[PDB]
Image 1 (cartoon, each protein chain N blue to C red):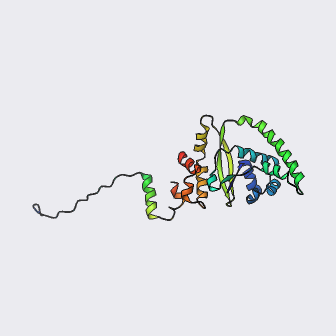
Image 2 (image 1 turned 135 degrees about the horizontal axis):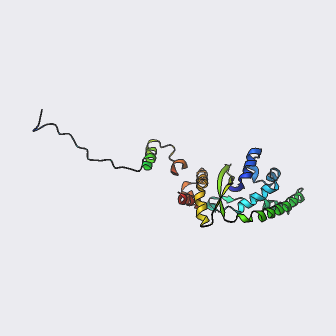
Image 3 (image 1 turned 180 degrees about the horizontal axis):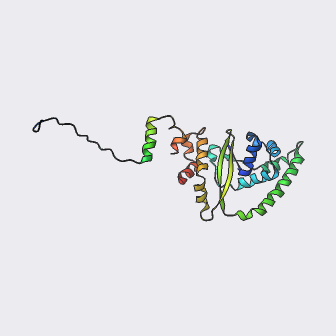
Length: 45
Length: 176
């Protein structure tokens, strides 16, 4: 039991911002699956 | 390549009958495998194709079979006079169609692209839609899946940066 002085954990500084469901779907493909990205099937989207 | 617009009825005949699509630009083959009416309808469908193709990328619209027949009828050879007789039949059948479908007037067609080699871009003229007010904009919105099909195929050989500067690429962006 420690009230006066105990552990002080770090507080996260960044808060995630909501994004557009379509930009996130395409972006995750852009970074995770860099194979179909250099084709019209992905570029058209 | 070279775009060859044909009605759905003609395209389905070619696919069902099993006509070599590769040799539809060779006058001597298409006239043997194509009826007089089909040849006239191909001419009419070419003359009703509203879009300007990317000439800067060497993509041309096919010369109609009637013109090719007319030219061969004036060139010495062993089939010249048979080709002249074919020309006369095409003109009478074409005039007969023009007098019947003149009422069509204010409509635009959906097109479907069926690529055949790198020298032939079969463009199937499908169902008509009625469009009187700004039919240019209506045609563009209707043919979304035609524009992206053309883009997908020319990006196989042409540089992406060059295709991006075409009117076909623009039409895609305007549609969506």
